[PDB]
Length: 129
Ligand SMILES: [Cl-]
Ligand SMILES: [Cl-]
Ligand SMILES: [Cl-]
Ligand SMILES: [Cl-]
Ligand SMILES: [Cl-]
Ligand SMILES: [Cl-]
Ligand SMILES: [N]
Ligand SMILES: [N]
Ligand SMILES: [N]
Ligand code: NA
Ligand SMILES: [Pt+2]
Ligand SMILES: [Pt+2]
Ligand SMILES: [Pt+2]
Ligand SMILES: [Pt+2]
Ligand SMILES: [Pt+2]
Image 1 (cartoon, rainbow, N blue to C red):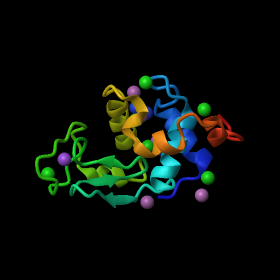
Image 2: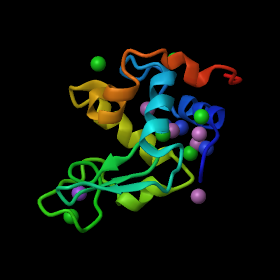
Image 3: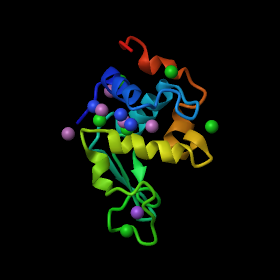
């Protein structure tokens, strides 16, 4: 599924991401935009053989099992395929664990390089929240 901007904002808010670990909703929508362009089916292969999955491009090195990332962990205890669902619950629940790991949203390289320090509120402007 390709979410609309405000559609994704609303789902993320409902699932408890707004100000989660102190990160405003706009940060999460911005991250999603530049990670997946709001596409739940987005996948991207990393040089180390791990794969990023879903709206927030959560990686199999640490966070999900795809049966094909040697040495990896599955700290969110999910198949990586669950991150591709039109239902974003697994993505959000896992993102909550990631952003609590100590580095906050810097865990998402695209967030650090394209969202951090920007007017992230713009990503939820206009939305009925
Ligand atoms: Cl957009
Ligand atoms: Cl915001
Ligand atoms: Cl594996
Ligand atoms: Cl959902
Ligand atoms: Cl959730
Ligand atoms: Cl933080
Ligand atoms: N949802
Ligand atoms: N939720
Ligand atoms: N949730
Ligand atoms: Na894994
Ligand atoms: Pt879909
Ligand atoms: Pt939902
Ligand atoms: Pt939820
Ligand atoms: Pt929660
Ligand atoms: Pt777009």
